[PDB]
Length: 620
Ligand SMILES: Nc1nc2c(ncn2[C@@H]2O[C@H](COP(=O)(O)OP(=O)(O)O)[C@@H](O)[C@H]2O)c(=O)[nH]1
Ligand SMILES: [Mn+2]
Ligand SMILES: [Mn+2]
Ligand SMILES: [Mn+2]
Image: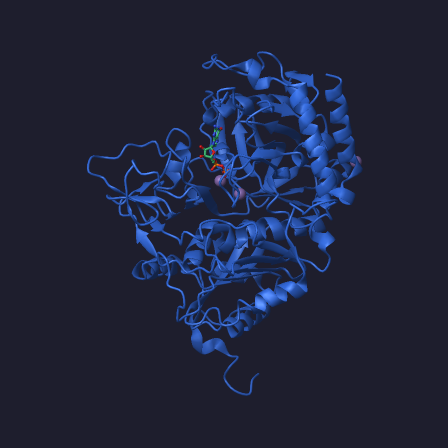
């Protein structure tokens, strides 16, 4: 009810009907409409018609450009201040800090950013009231995972950015069919605003609405709410990806007995017609997308992509670990993507794809560093800064975090079961990162508990994913450091508890390093499609082949166990060398890290593995 006309936003709905929404969806929409005060409300139906008008609208506003060279591809150029997912502005709200992060022993926690309810209410009320003035509030009903899938979860994102709507249509299942599937069911509440109410008080750069100063990405697992303000870029605004599928989801999985992980999923078929599914957790910019879409160099081997970033996993009745990709597309880094590195990505992004902050060629194409493709005579390049760009300048023409947003269905090697609601059985889990020294090409864990320790001990050199710079080696256990939804110590115990499941078929756990370098700073391993040779060894090890040698850090391939034909010039000694001096140092850093960062919440079995690894090394 009401005594005036300030609560019924029906007159501002320009597509859809507040009446057709489930009760709790309407309250969520109208309540924030009253708080944010949008000029219009647009309930997305996910149709092609809506998508086409949205793109046309953004093209008329100067928000996106049409890439004439390709089929329905578009380029967005962001404010240079809003070009990446901001980890320092990402917080998780719980009544108790210990629910979100372990209480460090000495210093500040790297496993998460906790904020109290009281502090968040002050930050929230300082940002959102009236933040959508003069703008349209889009209502995105989206499903993470195939509709009707047992591991699928439904969310509603409210946003004032048509760029977010278009991207969410690619990255999720979005439209009217989700509302019908949701019914009166529970849903994750996602609220997003670029934080630029009209009239504008700060001139917009590149027609990119954003509020860097007030940027804040908040998670409230207890209330099932994601609240993001100030940024329109990727992980900050596509709330189903990191905020939902990893942070919120990891907490739900802990409660409900499954796993939400930062893992690609790929199926691999060998020359004998046997096919296995693998999952791999690498930190950002460490090769998940290249591995998941690999073009294998070994004849008779086939790699198929289920997903390249997020895996939701759960043991089924038979004891198999089943995984689904909850996403609907790929949001991959553009630079470095070439025909020789990731030809399957090139084939995917040639249509129905949105590019952000890559360079544009004069003939309506895209360009970026590492594309490894010559341009025709006369073709000029416009940088992501919307300026004439020559290869002689030091400015890269594409931002290092530039992106393509492409539908997964267009991947030529998309797995025929990538949308199966039952998921795919995982028989192996891979951990890895950028280690320039010490860590061999591949080793296999000695047990489940050691495997969990291997994931917890993961380290990798600073890349260009968050706001980290320089050449530093940091910890990123399970490749989840930016994404833990709850106490990491409890996360370890959750992983360890899977070994207690009856009839559980635990997958083998491997650790790979594509990035070891020699004394000259040159990669010892060619990588890319050649990684199929490493997958072949894992494949045989899962079948039980006696191809492993025992070392202090785990099992490594026997001599001549790796198919190295066609290479031969590879320095195998330095590539699999295990140095006592290096690993003595490695255990100590892991020890100091786990002791400080996990402290009282470190499971004993993890501490035992650390002690056991320290002992085996000391006997070298
Ligand atoms: N040396 C080497 N580099 C790689 C390999 N795979 C990927 N890369 C590089 O790592 C960067 C990011 O790769 P990407 O697949 O997007 O990583 P993701 O963010 O985990 O999906 C790209 O620029 C690639 O050139 C590899 O096997 N060897
Ligand atoms: Mn990722
Ligand atoms: Mn990627
Ligand atoms: Mn145990």
